[PDB]
Image (tube, rainbow over all chains, first blue to last red):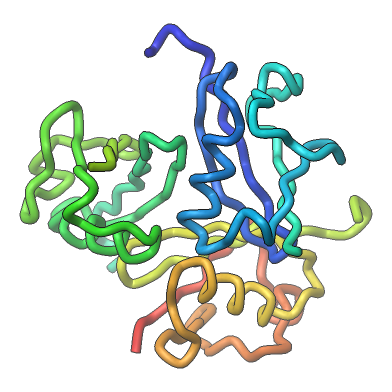
Length: 78
Length: 78
Length: 78
């Protein structure tokens, strides 16, 4: 709802691409990772998502990882 | 041309994704809906586009729907 | 690294889509063109990339083409 804290996030690939997401602060990042792989034509097993150098787990949320609005998640291809 | 009113629009999926479009104010939204389905790997029959709760028809234009620059179109998956 | 000049670029298709990239100023635009075709579901032979009306070659870089931060590259479908 409009009463949640939504956080804007940028997902930046090593290929230069920057894709935007907006999700609630307590939403598991699996939501974003699955969406990203589906929409950008990538497979989960071939890419790795990291934030401030640490890999992001399925149930990690922006709030849990202490993300702030407009933070960037890095994507590496494997 | 540079003499038209171009409107920036955000298309926000229920999956958290936010995809940007820029089209002239009198352009039918079919342009955006087809482009979105092609580029994001979605099929038209499986997604529904709405603006301020109302479904968007093929020939509806941002001007006709009284959209403003930076408005958001919502996408639901079916 | 953080000591390079990274340039934000927008790639605007004739279909209204606007896709964002961030690459170093001396990086060949082949990086962006390949990424764009892969992610947006397009084939290189079917699209043409231009900047200020001139086609972009594989090894052209934003700096070489005298691009500035937030410039737009145009994409035409063939």
